RNA sequence: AAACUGCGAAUGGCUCAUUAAAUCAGUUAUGGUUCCUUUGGUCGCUCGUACUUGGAUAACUGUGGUAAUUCU
RNA sequence: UGGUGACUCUAGAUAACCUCGGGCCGAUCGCACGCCGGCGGCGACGACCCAUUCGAACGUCUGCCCUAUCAACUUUCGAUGGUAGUCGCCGUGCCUACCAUGGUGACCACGGGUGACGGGGAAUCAGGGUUCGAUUCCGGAGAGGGAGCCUGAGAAACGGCUACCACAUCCAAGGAAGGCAGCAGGCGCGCAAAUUA
RNA sequence: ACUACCGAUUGGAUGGUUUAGUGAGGCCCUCGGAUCGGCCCCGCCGGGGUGCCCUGGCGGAGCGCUGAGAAG
């Protein structure tokens, strides 16, 4: 069913899947109600989260996290983990003895919700700070924009 | 003792780090509560801040819910059949959170017959004590028989719940965490969750 | 540390207490109470350093535990009891009443008030919540909980409350054009009318305030205490009226005062 | 070995030194609060149990 | 006086061995937690011998043990 | 109902549960005594919960000296991520089970060193810098070395306890007691530092 | 005669990473049950509603029912 790929039954804790309904409603349509919310800072909840079917407890829009604290950006560099990506933040650090700059970088592991598809290497991602979700992830993807050179 | 600090582990680069302080009492871990089925034996724990944790070591009775119709009853745990974390805990009959349990179904059948007045989990022979014809086949008034008619208009439940009542023991999921609560509360499995757990149990064999 | 602290070093004390360096190594260390440690004036500093009835801390204790000092109408014998903004101090033996409000330099002025003005005080509403059985509560800036407030009273509004009973008697909204006093930050002690509140979601709001002399200054929303409705304050103000003079006009005023007398 | 004998009804007590192993075999290999008839302790202790 | 009970002894004082994104500083978060105390609120909101309940244990009295202890 | 920028918030309703190692709903103490046996004013002490105060504890972003005669490291023994739980005051590979093979690195990882506790700060001073900051304020760490607990709101406490390691005190030889990187003081060390007031 | 290096002796001791094994002491769990108390039974027995019952103090046995509980 492309949903129950685990050894426990995956469901959204807030929605109830065992409502007692009539035969006409049974023959009408078999669509579950879906829990979603807004990451309310001028961030639009995507349609793939509202109309989707996936289950992710660490998703900003459908899971159990809240976005509070910093909001940063990065470029996607690696996408080889399961529901998390590794992004890169480049910056310039000012050495004031020389009055010059050196280029520095920080690698950041962020949680990518399944509602963001067609995320490529090099696309600009906007992440927001949440509570600790694993040992090394603290930020959660909220927006994706493509690279300006790509059509 | 058991320490659940983050500084004993390695760094994100994989290098090892030196501790700058020794183990603190706010970083402690306690030995696990392997709650089992048996007559009630629970131990209270003093925790951080002078508050109380209840550590259940032997439990046999909880309360469980039909959520389709919002009715819960205090009943008995009978057996452990599935655990998504470890099958060794099924073999040891360990009560944890989200372990699949089968429980006694007598209060639920009792409420269903005292409310909807239809037989539940009954054989073709249907030999009943006279209290059951008193409950199922009482004498009522016009308003009451009418209200019962629109009550049995929708009093049809799933065939799988019928099959489990035919068997006599209901499947449920323990939703409380018993080593911290001293209770093994939960909810009766229904719907796609019920077919999931049935096919996983059958796929174990 | 292994637990909470009980001592305050004198150089680490709040600077607006105006303690000196050589009297001791310790400062009076305010008790826990309705005010923060950094935003209060303890009773020993008031009775000894400012008001000068006492010469030592032992004399402060002898004054306080003869049951002479009321704070907000309640007799206090804790010598380090944290008194703070808008708190009324009453000495019935000498017939004196005070409100702890700020100078233009950010220090608690010795502000004498009329005994009818000592009947009430103002509080800034810090939270509104509904508790069990649907009962609305407000929490003020001085740790007061009042049940059943007016439904129009919101957070950042100012209640005018009666010290005899403790109930809500009047209130003032947060609105552009109301009079306010600044209780934190670099503009501590200044008074003016609110002219613009800009909102930053997920962050601190910035309120713009205009002085009675036309000077304008901004603060955070946490630092604003609404005092009077529109233009007239609902309490007595100190000798300076919230007008921060620069160092040049303060020198000129000092020289004119020295010239006029002497 | 010495014996600290106490009598609670009149609340009176006394220390008595007895050195003969035959008199102490009535006390050996038994536990605290094990009731013993102290007959072999002396001629005056016939009906006395301790 | 003693002794039981309550509280404090987790503050203060000392030193700089450890410790290299660790500590620490500035900035943010707890919408992810605990909090003696102070202060305010709540404390006939429960439909089910009381004009006062029970057993001890110190201090005290008396007998003691060990070379020795703030032992008993 | 009420709130936030955003709740799975707060409040409401239903069905029940409510731990014997047990959650509240006062068998407590003083002073003045007074009204129509019954009604009472000040307090003190307790008290489940909520808020506040004093914190604490875990996270965010940015920032540190020398070394390549340290160039690949982490990953069986958790390394990086997912799902379910355990433990924990709580978030979390904190731990367990099953999975995926990931995570970091010439923008210097990993390793090693430092005559390295970090800052506020000090000397110099046209300016940039250079050297110093064991040391009275703030934060951390430790109590001979390790480790483990009890009590308590709070400690992995050492002017608390229990072991082992290294030292070491008394003894009738069975046993008992120990921790000055507190104030003085002593020995040692040394070029190097005060009174058992 | 002096200064400064190498050095057989697994020379003797000591420490830090580790392979294998042993492991004090606390904590948790499952037992254990020295001791200590209550109920029931009976005996010595006081009163009433007039031998039915209970009232209070002492003793006796019953692995009867139990509750607290040390060492291990």
Image: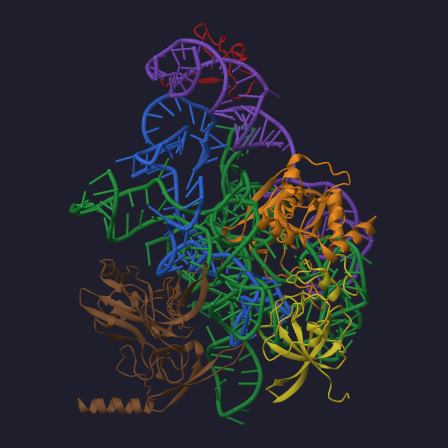
Chain colours: A yellow, B orange, C brown, D red, E blue, F green, G purple
Residue C193 visible to the viewer = yes
- Give x and y (percent) for residue C104: 33, 82
- Give x and y (percent) for residue F123: 47, 81
Name the residue nearer the viewer: C262 or A121: A121
- Give x and y (percent) for residue F30: 24, 44
Res. C76 image quadrant: bottom left
Q: Residue furthest front?
A: B142
Name the residue nearer the viewer: C59 or A46: A46
- Give x and y (percent) for residue A73: 66, 80
Taking the image as shown, residue B55 lies to the left or right of residue D4, namely right
Taking the image as shown, residue F163 lies to the left or right of residue F106, namely left
Res. E48 image quadrant: top left
Residue at image position (60%, 69%) is A66
Q: Identify whether F163 is placed above or below F54.
A: above
Taking the image as shown, residue F66 lies to the left or right of residue E56, namely right
Q: Identify whether C201 is placed above or below F137.
A: below
Name the residue nearer the viewer: C175 or A53: A53
Q: Residue furthest top?
A: D43
Taking the image as shown, residue G65 lies to the left or right of residue C120, namely right
């Amino acid at each position: 069913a492309d949903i129950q790929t685990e050894r426990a039954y995956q469901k959204q804790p807030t929605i109830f899947q065992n409502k007692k309904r009539v035969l006409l409603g049974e023959t009408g349509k078999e669509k579950l109600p879906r829990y979603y919310k807004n990451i309310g800072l001028g961030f639009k909840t995507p349609k793939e989260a509202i109309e989707g079917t996936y289950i992710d407890k660490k998703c900003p829009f459908t899971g159990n996290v809240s976005i509070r604290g910093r909001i940063l950006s990065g470029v996607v560099t690696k996408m080889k983990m399961q529901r998390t990506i590794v992004i890169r933040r480049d910056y310039l650090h000012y050495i004031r003895k020389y009055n010059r700059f050196e280029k520095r970088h920080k690698n950041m592991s962020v949680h990518l919700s399944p509602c963001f598809r067609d995320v490529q290497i090099g696309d600009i991602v906007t992440v927001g700070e949440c509570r600790p979700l694993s040992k090394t992830v603290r930020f959660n993807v909220l927006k994706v924009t493509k690279a300006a050179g790509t059509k | 003792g058991i320490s659940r600090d983050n500084w004993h582990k390695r760094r994100k680069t994989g290098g090892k780090r030196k501790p700058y302080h020794k183990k603190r009492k706010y970083e402690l871990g306690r030995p696990a509560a392997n709650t089992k089925i048996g007559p009630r034996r629970i131990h209270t724990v003093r925790v951080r801040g002078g508050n109380k944790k209840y550590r259940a070591l032997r439990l046999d009775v909880g309360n469980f819910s039909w959520g389709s119709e919002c009715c819960t009853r205090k009943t008995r745990i009978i057996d452990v059949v599935y655990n998504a974390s470890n099958n060794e805990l099924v073999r040891t009959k360990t009560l944890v959170k989200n372990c699949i349990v089968l429980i006694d179904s007598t209060p639920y059948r009792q409420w269903y017959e005292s409310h909807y007045a239809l037989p539940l989990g009954r054989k073709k022979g249907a030999k009943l004590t006279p209290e059951e014809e008193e409950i199922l086949n009482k004498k009522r008034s016009k308003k009451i028989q009418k209200k019962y008619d629109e009550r049995k208009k929708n009093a049809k439940i799933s065939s799988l719940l019928e099959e489990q009542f035919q068997q006599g023991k209901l499947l449920a999921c323990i939703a409380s965490r018993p080593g911290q609560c001293g209770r093994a509360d939960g909810y009766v499995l229904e719907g796609k969750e019920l077919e999931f757990y049935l096919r996983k149990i059958k796929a174990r064999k | 540390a292994r637990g909470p602290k009980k001592h305050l070093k004198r150089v680490a004390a709040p600077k607006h207490w105006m303690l000196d360096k050589l009297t001791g190594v310790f400062a009076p260390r305010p008790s826990t109470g309705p005010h923060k440690l950094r935003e209060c004036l303890p009773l020993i500093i008031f009775l000894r350093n400012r008001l000068k009835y006492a010469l030592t801390g032992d004399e402060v204790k002898k004054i306080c535990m003869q049951r002479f000092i009321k704070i907000d109408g309640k007799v206090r014998t804790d010598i380090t009891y944290p008194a703070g903004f808008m708190d009324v101090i009453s000495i019935d033996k000498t017939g004196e009443n005070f409100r702890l409000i700020y100078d233009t330099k950010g220090r608690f002025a010795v502000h004498r008030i009329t005994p009818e003005e000592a009947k009430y005080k103002l509080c800034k509403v810090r939270k509104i919540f509904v508790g069990t059985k649907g009962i609305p509560h407000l929490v003020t800036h001085d740790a007061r909980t009042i049940r059943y407030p007016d439904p129009l009273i919101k957070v950042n509004d100012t209640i005018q409350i009666d010290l005899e009973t403790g109930k809500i008697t009047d209130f003032i909204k947060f609105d552009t054009g109301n009079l306010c006093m600044v209780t934190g930050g670099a503009n501590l002690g200044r008074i003016g009318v609110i002219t613009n509140r800009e909102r930053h979601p997920g962050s601190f709001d910035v309120v713009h305030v205009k002085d009675a002399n036309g000077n304008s200054f901004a603060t955070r929303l946490s630092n604003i205490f609404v005092i009077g409705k529109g233009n007239k304050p609902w309490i007595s103000l100190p000798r300076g009226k919230g007008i921060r003079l620069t160092i040049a006009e303060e020198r000129d005023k000092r020289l004119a005062a020295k010239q006029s007398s002497g | 070995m010495k014996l600290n004998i106490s009598f609670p009804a009149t609340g009176c007590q006394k220390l008595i030194e007895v050195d003969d192993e035959r008199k102490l075999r009535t006390f050996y290999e038994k536990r605290m609060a094990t009731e013993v008839a102290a007959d072999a302790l002396g001629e005056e202790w016939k009906g006395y149990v301790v």
